[PDB]
Every structure is written in structure tokens, then in C-alpha cells.
Image (cartoon, coloured by chain):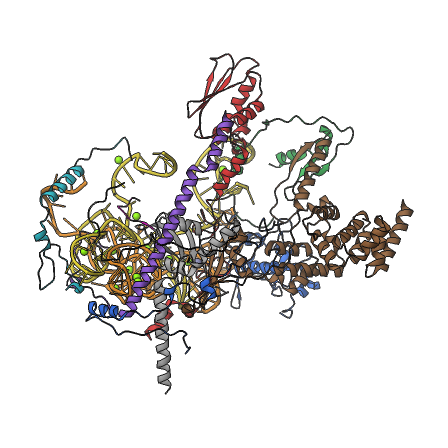
Chain colours: C purple, D red, E green, F blue, G brown, H cyan, I yellow, J orange
Amino acid sequence: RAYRGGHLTIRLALGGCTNRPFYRIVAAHSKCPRDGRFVEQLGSYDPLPNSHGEKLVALNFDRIRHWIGCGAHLSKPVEKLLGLSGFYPLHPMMITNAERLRRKRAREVLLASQKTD
Amino acid sequence: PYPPLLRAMILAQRQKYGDTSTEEPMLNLERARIDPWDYPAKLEAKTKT
Amino acid sequence: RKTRHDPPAKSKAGRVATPPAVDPTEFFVLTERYRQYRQTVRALRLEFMSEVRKKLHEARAGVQAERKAQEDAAEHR
Amino acid sequence: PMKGRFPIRRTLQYLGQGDVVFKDSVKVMTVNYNTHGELGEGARKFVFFNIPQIQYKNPWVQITMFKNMTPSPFLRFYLDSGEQVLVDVESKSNKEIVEHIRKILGKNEETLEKEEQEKKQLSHPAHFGPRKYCLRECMCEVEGQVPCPGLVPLPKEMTGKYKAALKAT
Amino acid sequence: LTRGLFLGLSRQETHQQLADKKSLHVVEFREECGPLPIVVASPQGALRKDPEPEDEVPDITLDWEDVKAAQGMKRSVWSGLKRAAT
Amino acid sequence: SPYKDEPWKYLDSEEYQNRYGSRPVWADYRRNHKGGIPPQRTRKMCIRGNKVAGNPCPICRDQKLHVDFRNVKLLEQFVCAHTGIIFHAPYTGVCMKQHKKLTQAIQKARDHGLLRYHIPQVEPRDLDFSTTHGAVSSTPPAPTLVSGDPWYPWYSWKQPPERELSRLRRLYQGRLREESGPPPELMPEV
Amino acid sequence: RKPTFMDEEVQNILIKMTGLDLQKIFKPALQELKPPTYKLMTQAQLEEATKQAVEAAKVRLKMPPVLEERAPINDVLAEDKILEGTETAKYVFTDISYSIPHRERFIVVREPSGTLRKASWEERDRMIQVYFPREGRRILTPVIFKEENLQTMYSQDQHVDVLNLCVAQFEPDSAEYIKIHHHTYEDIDKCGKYDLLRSTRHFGGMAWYFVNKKKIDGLLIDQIQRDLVSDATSLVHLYHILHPDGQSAQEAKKQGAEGLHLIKVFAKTEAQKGAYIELTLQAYQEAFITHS
Amino acid sequence: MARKKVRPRLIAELARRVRALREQRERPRDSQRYALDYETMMRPHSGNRLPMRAW
RNA sequence: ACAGGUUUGGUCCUGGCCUUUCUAUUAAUUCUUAAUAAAAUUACACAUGCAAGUAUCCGCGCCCCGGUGAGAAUGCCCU
RNA sequence: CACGGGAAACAGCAGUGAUAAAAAUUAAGCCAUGAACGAAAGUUUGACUAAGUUAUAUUAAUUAGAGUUGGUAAAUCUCG
Ligand SMILES: [Mg+2]
Ligand SMILES: [Mg+2]
Ligand SMILES: [Mg+2]
Ligand SMILES: [Mg+2]
Ligand SMILES: [Mg+2]
Ligand SMILES: [Mg+2]
Ligand SMILES: [Mg+2]
Ligand SMILES: [Mg+2]
Ligand SMILES: [Mg+2]
Ligand SMILES: [Mg+2]
Ligand SMILES: [Mg+2]
Ligand SMILES: [Mg+2]
Ligand SMILES: [Mg+2]
Ligand SMILES: [Mg+2]
Ligand SMILES: [Mg+2]
Ligand SMILES: [Mg+2]
Ligand SMILES: [Mg+2]
Ligand SMILES: [Mg+2]
Ligand SMILES: [Zn+2]
Ligand SMILES: [Zn+2]
């Protein structure tokens, strides 16, 4: 329907099943609902590991770069997914929470070593 | 340098069309200059051109 | 969700938000990582803009399109 | 269809098997014909048989009949650019009229499979959603992934209530 | 029903009689066998060299129930009912 | 059942030929129902515990019949010879549980090759078979890849200037949090 | 200039090798049947229908390509030790579009250690199947291609269906396709079941495997037993084409041998059991001279 | 869209007219708009409380 | 519709009604545990609690999500 | 329609009266997706996620009751 404003957004749409989520990579309007009407479905992302132990991601490269080139904004998880893809550089939130896991796990190692004594 | 997999498409596309030259493709940043946050935004209405 | 004409909550009327504590060195490296991150993403985005301009300009006025136009006109004649 | 002199021409197979598709600039197609004389027999058979097929394959193109005004039957094509194409029939039979129209102004065969080829690009197999537009609905239905919780129950360790119970204890 | 059924099945025309009355070969085109021309009957006697007149629009009597079944407009709930063994 | 691990022995037995003969098992069974049209769904399960309810199914009235992938002669009776599809449950007369078991058994037999079924001739997947493209062939490595350095200089950690730390301490005084040093290179495990 | 499978000489050799059996190539199949269509045809229309069925048979016996074993893909596009422990599983990124051919697609794996690398061939083909459905391929490796199930189908002489499942499931440059085809040709070589694959499009594959594996003995015995000897010396000429430096080829060039002399030279020279080929050819010669 | 049974609404245009007239007449001055109470840090005109980083 | 029951001392034809098949709400009787899907009497009136905030003040958002089918033959498709 | 007048508005999430044959918790979190804001750590979100209740519907078993027995239409003996 007709909205007062908003922008074009490439984001993750949550469909799927109870305790089995699924995100469809969706280029749509910002002001529409999460599972509402979209412009184009680009890709998919499987949040769960399979029998092969793989999390499976599909991206429609030419259409994604066309939408970004004509001005589609990206959300934080899809920039994270593109940073892991290597079409975009690594997202500094992945960088900083990685170093936060390094600091936390090193502090846990030190706490375990102190609790051993 | 490019992000690596985009750099892989650049190498693959030039190898597909036969460009033998192995020069590293470079992303140029003269239009990428970003004025930081405490610049005061223009409150005057921009004239459409 | 709420609406323009409804009153706000009485409990949250006297409530103001609290920003979290700041780790200064981590904040500074974080701020830099956004600066050259947004630099790289901006350069990539204007590169995709140039690609969109190239593809649209070719789809409008490509040499193949004038051959198609000349061929269909010649066949019609 | 029991009624009618030739009941087979009113079926969907006859309407869909007539292959004449005009160009996009074609707007008006006009048949002036006569109902007397052996000369207009081919034009009368053309009106009786093929104009439903051409009108089915070109729903937006106007097609108009006129009877007994001009002694010789003819067809007249009115285009977008004011262009008037006259096809004169006096002794040509129905199939010759069909190939004559399809050769003067129709759509080329290669243009037909390319038109259905960018028509078939719109339905990409990699999309997901409803059955009416997409092949799959769940990602669950794919053989290698996690089976769907409405058919195969999930293990306890993945379940959110067990996660909340272990976090609260 | 019994009298009409026996009259209809006694007025049945075989492929041998059709080939004898037309003096032409009759060919069965199976769909599971592809484009292979299975010949099931052959005209004994003199075989005619003149082909059949190919009419662009055949003149046959069509049934509206059969055409409606072919076009998929038969949405009756009793047509697709699963039933017992023969 | 004394047969158990071999279900085809009762199929080859003399008692099967004496009772059923060359006709299938479900040929002599007739389902009782409410009118001239049977319901689309049969009885769900016919034996509940030790109790056999009413007229049993053609499989279920003979307890020496075993629904398995090992016997092909039993499973062929529920598969059409010409059409090559599994017969539906109202066509035969078995219960829904044994019909699901039959469907799984025919699927496992076709996956194990014990039952013939139609395999269409399939064209090769791609038109041109080329490894020459850089998607499958190896690309030359990056200058940052051969040197062992991260892809960008800012992927690692850099010690910030002390005047910038003092400036951030001045701007966020009162709400400050304790600073941390460089991160470890490799984590140890618990 | 080594001989390849797509050369015109070897293609026409295999086309005249496989023969044409209309009833065998057009068999009533096990899908859902429909009532056949009848028409009245003249004799000339009957040979017209027969000949259009002949080119339909030729485009049905358009043979599958056979290739060598592909090289594994071991290329790492980026290494990141900073994401060594952030994730437990591995990520697969797949290029999807309608206009890119499937060999040119980018199938890229992030390992849990943080390496951006190229995927291997098996997971690459698995991704191609998952994000591009087609009939005949299972995503996981089927149980049917285990050796016990292969021996079950081969004792039930289902070799044409096994090869059809192999070409439908796997890719011709893969290792599993090669080993399944080779084990099939070995077992039909041991059992002498060459008559099953005569009018099948997979005849050229086992002929090519035999001419590279230097086992022409049993196949030549089978062809002389089925009394088709012009195609047998066509097979010998195929052997001489694929082995230009062979002592049979030099003896053939020295003697200027015809077809039957060519078969005799091959049997006396390079056949492992040439006595069987010689006695079978002698029996064929005396039988054909007595009956003609 | 356009139909043959559309009726000429006037009150919506009149209300937009009166609303524009009233905002142009009673447009708030910057002094009463931006005057501040320095203990509560709460705006008497807009009802907004100041953030603590600007306190 | 693969049809069946039903007019008459009885037969044939025409012609209605009902049964056999599937789904959804309510009621009655009965009822053991899980998983999944769905929660639906009301455009009648509402006690109470929450559902629009963020941000170095300006600003930006504030039926955007979500809810309902009252009204209108409204409207579907296309420039 | 909403300038104005009746008049103090849940056709938001929960719940309460009236009414109807018609009966979900006056509940936990933004941990994940979307939205809003901010340069940003981040904040909010009765959307949502995870649950609670209900044979309303499918599946698995832990479970045995309901309908019917003149014909259509499977199936009855003795009493009143
Ligand atoms: Mg849901
Ligand atoms: Mg409201
Ligand atoms: Mg009646
Ligand atoms: Mg009467
Ligand atoms: Mg009576
Ligand atoms: Mg109820
Ligand atoms: Mg504000
Ligand atoms: Mg709505
Ligand atoms: Mg009205
Ligand atoms: Mg409510
Ligand atoms: Mg109430
Ligand atoms: Mg209810
Ligand atoms: Mg209640
Ligand atoms: Mg109640
Ligand atoms: Mg709460
Ligand atoms: Mg949140
Ligand atoms: Mg958050
Ligand atoms: Mg139920
Ligand atoms: Zn699912
Ligand atoms: Zn049973």
C-alpha cells in the first residue's frame, strides 16, 4: 500500500517453523512488515547446521549489487553475512565481538587456572 | 585492495575475456571521503537540479 | 504499537534513558573501524552505481539496439 | 459443444493451436468481404475459421468485419504510426492467407522462443515461498536439512523451553 | 441399458474391418512407446496409393461433457473419488 | 511368527499357494462401508494391543505376512504392472498404518533396487565441460595472502595515541569503564 | 593429436557399432499410460513415420560424454585467524542466477577456523543440486550405489538402469561416475552380457573403456557369435585408430589386410586368448560358406 | 480511483484549510518554544526531558 | 457421479426430494501424554497494567508494525 | 468528511460487563529477525521469540469410548 516515506531495504525475513527458523534474504521497502509484500527475493540463509555440519547461504549477486547500486540500505545481519561472504569486508561488529570472545575466554582460562589451585 | 571474493570475480571476468595482465585491481577512494558526525547539516532546502 | 494521539506511560514519564559505560581504547579503535569501513562500503557502492549507469546506458543506447532497430525497419520496408 | 456447424473450432485446443502473433505496433485488423461469388470463398473460410485464433493470440488488437460494400475482399492493417497495410485477396485460399499474413507482419519464431525465454527467467528455481509461485515452502523439505517439526519432532537439546529451563536453573 | 450395451458392443468396428474397408494401413501411436509406428492391422488385397484427404478443420461430433473433462472444467467432487477394487 | 527373518519363505510355501493361489492377497477381501461409495480414508489401525477389531485387513488377517523390503512377491501385488504406481488404500483394503508401512517398504525396495521402476533417460547436466574458468581453477594469490598479513591493515589491533585516550576519558568522565590491553592471538581451551 | 571421444571417425564407428533396433529402443515404459491414437496411413506415409522414428532414435542415442578424473580444488581466498572460534559450523556461499553456467558458479566455504576457501567438488555439486532442483539427483549419496546393491542389480541384470541412474545422478568428470561405470563394464565383461547394451546409448562408453583397457577378446567373441562381422572389423579398425603404435597396426599396414584378415591378424597377434577368436571365426566361416 | 458514484467531500479540504490557517496563525515563537526549566531539565512547551549527557 | 432409494394393481418416459464423498463451527457423550498448526460471537461499553522511543538539548519517528471487516458493488487487470 | 457538535472512545496486547450456540495468560524477555533513534558502544519494542490454556485439525504412541443393526447401507437374540 501507499506509505508516506521510507527507503528500500535488503534485510532478513523470518519465516519458517517453531524452533526451526528460516530467513529469506529480501529486498523490500522499509515501512512494510517483515513478512509482508516485497520487491525481490534475493537469497536465503539456513540458521541450522545440516547432517554435513554446514550453514547454507544463497545470494543473488548481480541483483544484490544492482539494488545496492541504485541505493538499497542494508541491515546489520545482512552486512555480517556479506562480510563473511567476502563480497563485502568483515563487519567491525564481528571484529569486536570476536575480540570480546578472545578476552572472555582468556579470562575464563585464567579463572580456571586460579580455581585449579 | 578489493574484498577477496569480489576480487575473484574481477580476475575471473578478465580471464574469461582473455586479459592476461595480472595487475592487482585497486578500489579508488577519492569519492569515498566521509565528513564526520559533528558537521552541521544543511537545514536550507536543496534546489533540485 | 502506539499512536500519535495516545498519552505516554506514567511510569516512564519521569524516566530518562541511560547510556552504557565506555571502554575508551576499544571505543576509539571501534570508531576508526567504522570510518574506513564506511569508506570502503561507500567506494564499493559508487562502483556498483557506475555499473548500474553502464548497464542502463547500454540497455538504452547500445550498438546492438541500433542494429535491432535498423534491421526491423529494413524488414518492415 | 454439440451446437454449431463446426463444433471443433470452439475448443481451447483450436484457439490455442492457431499460431499468428502480430507485432506490438499492430492496432486494427479489418476484413472487408462478400458473401456471394466463388471468389470470396477463401475470405469466407478465413472469417469462419482463423479470426478466433488470431484474436486469441492477439487479445489487445481490434479485429473488425464488414460485409458487402466493396466488390473485392481485402484485409487492412492500421498501425501505431498511421501506417496502413493492404492485403488483397481475390483467389487466394485460407492457408495461403495465413502464411501471407504471418510473413508480412507476424512475430519471428526466434523472437517467440526468446520471448518465452525471458518469460521463463521470471520463475527462478532458487526462490522459496507459496506453491503457486515457488517450488518449495519450507527449507525443511530439502533432504539434507533439519526435518520439519510438524512431521519429525526435534531433539530436546535444541528446544527453547529446555534452554530456558537450563538457564533458569 | 443391457440391450443398448449389447447393441453398441455388437456394432463395434475392428481394426481389420477398418483397414479392409479403407484399403490403407492403420498405425497405432502409443504414447509410452514414443514415435514408433506400431502397425496392428494390414489391408489384405490391393493397397491404395492415394493418401487420405487432409482436412484442416475436421467435421466431427463433439460432446460437451468430454470437452469439459478435457479442458479441466469438471470440478465435480464425485469424479475423482477413490473407490474399491474391480 | 516362525518365519521372521525370511518373509519370502512363506511366499514360496505350499500353504500360500493352497490358500491364496495365483490371485493376489487383497482379491478376496471386501470392505464394509456405509453406502455405494467407500470413504476416502480407511480404518487407521485395525489391531489395538491384543484385540483384533472386526473384519481384518488382507495383510493383517494373516500374521505370517511380513511387510519388508526383502520380499518382492508380496510388494508387487500392491504395485500396478503397467502404470507402475502404488495402489491407494481404498483400492486394496488395508489399514492406514500398514499402508504407510507398505509405502515405506516399496520406497526402500526401489532405493535398494529390488523392485523395477521407470528411470527416464536424462541428458548431461551442463552443455560445455570446462575447468578453465577461475571459479573452479585456482586464482593467483594476493600480495597480502603471500605475506601472511590480514587482508586489511585495520583487521588487527593497533595501540591508540595516549592523547586520544585522554580526550575520550575527558569526554566520558564519570561514566568510564576500565580499559583493556591487546587481545590474545590464540585462545586456549577449557 | 591423440584420438578423443568426440572425433568424427570414432563417432561414426560407434554409430554403426551400436546398430538400430526399433523395438528395443522404443519399449513400453512404466509411467502413467494414456490411450493411443490411431490414424490411416498410406505405405509412403508408413516409411515416412518409420524414418522420422529413425532420427528420433538417433537423437535418443546421442551418447553421453566421457572425460577423465577432475583435479581437486584446493584454493584459499582469505585467511582470518581472528574468527578461529566465533562459529562452530561452516558457512557455504553459493552464486545463484539464471544466466551464469553451472561450471562458472562461485561456491565458497568459510571454515570455522576462519578461512575463506573454495569448496571441493562433492559439496559444490551438492550445492548445485540443492539450489537447482532437477529430477534424478538425490542430495545425499544414495544407498543404491553401494557394492551390495550394485551386485543385487547386476544379478538382476539391471545394468542399463544402473548406468542411467549413474549418468542422471553424478557428473561425467567425477570420480564416482568413473568407478561405477568401470565396475559395471568389468562385471559385464566377466558375465558376457554385451547384448543388453547393444541398442543402448551407453554402448560407446564400454567400447571406449575396452579399447583403452586392451580387452577386446570377449566382445569380439560375442559379435562373431551374433554374426555381425563388418562391425567387428570396424571395432578392429577402431582399435588400430586408438593404438597407432601397435604391432597389430604395423602387421596390418604390412599385409594390407581386409576385414576378415584384419580380425585374423588381431587374433593371432594381440588377443590374449586368440585361440577362441580363431576357432569362433573358423566356425562362422564354415557355417556362412555352407549356408550361403 | 474514479467512479461514477463519487460524492463531493468538502469538509476534508475545509479542515486542511483551517488547520493550515491555525498553524500559520499560532506558530510558536522560539522563546516560548525553547524556554527551559533548569532543575527538572524538562521542556514546558514540548514536554521532552533532556538527555543526561547534556545535563 | 460408476450411482442408489422413492410416484403406480403393474410397465415405460418425464420430473423433484433424500442417501452415499470432503471440510469448518456449535452442542451431546467420552477423554491418556507429547509435538506441530490455529484460536474465530459482536464497528456494543469499558476498572486496571503495559504496548514510541532514541539522542550532548535542535532534530528524527509517533495506525510505521499491529487490529477489524462497519461501510461501499464496492472492485480484479492494465496505462 | 471532522472545521464544529454529541462526548470523554482498547475494531493494540492482556482482561471485565452486556450479548451470543460460540469462553487463550490481567504472563517472561528483546537472546534471534524487523522497525525507530544515535557517528557509536547501544536503548525501546504486548511486532516478534520462547512458553501457558483449549481434542479445533495432523502425527506418534502411553489410550477405550461413541454411533448403528427393516431397505438404501456393513451388521440382532430374548423380554416389556
Ligand atoms: Mg509461526
Ligand atoms: Mg489506537
Ligand atoms: Mg430419480
Ligand atoms: Mg401418479
Ligand atoms: Mg406401492
Ligand atoms: Mg466447544
Ligand atoms: Mg525528540
Ligand atoms: Mg489489514
Ligand atoms: Mg447500498
Ligand atoms: Mg483485546
Ligand atoms: Mg465476558
Ligand atoms: Mg471456539
Ligand atoms: Mg468458559
Ligand atoms: Mg469463561
Ligand atoms: Mg514485559
Ligand atoms: Mg530486539
Ligand atoms: Mg538488539
Ligand atoms: Mg479430532
Ligand atoms: Zn518446516
Ligand atoms: Zn490392518
Indicate the position of residue D169 as horizontal and vertical percent values.
33, 75
Indicate the position of residue F11 as horizontal and vertical percent values.
67, 62
Please determine whether, in this image, residue C46 is positioned above or below residue G153: above
- Residue E7, by quadrant, is top right
Q: Nearer the viewer, residue I71 or C54?
A: C54
Asked if residue A17 shows in the view, the reply is no
Indicate the position of residue H53 as horizontal and vertical percent values.
18, 64
- Residue J13, by quadrant, is bottom left
Tell me what residue is drawn at x 18 percent, y 39 percent: H12
Asked if residue F131 shows in the view, the reply is yes
Query: Which quadrant: the N terminus of chain C?
Result: bottom left
Tell me what residue is drawn at x 84 percent, y 48 percent: G258
Q: Nearer the viewer, residue H5 or A83?
A: A83
* Residue that protrudes farthest toward the right in the picture: G290
Indicate the position of residue B31 as horizontal and vertical percent values.
33, 51
Please determine whether, in this image, residue A94 is positioned above or below residue G287: below
- Say left or right for F6 vs C11: right
Please determine whether, in this image, residue G247 is positioned above or below residue F158: above
- Say left or right for G88 vs J29: right
Q: Nearer the viewer, residue E61 or F23?
A: E61
Range shown magenta: A2-8
Count all numbered tags in the image, as a single digit.
0
Task: Let me know if residue A6 is in the magenta part.
Answer: yes
- Say left or right for I7 vs A98: right
Task: Let me know if residue D102 is in the magenta part.
Answer: no
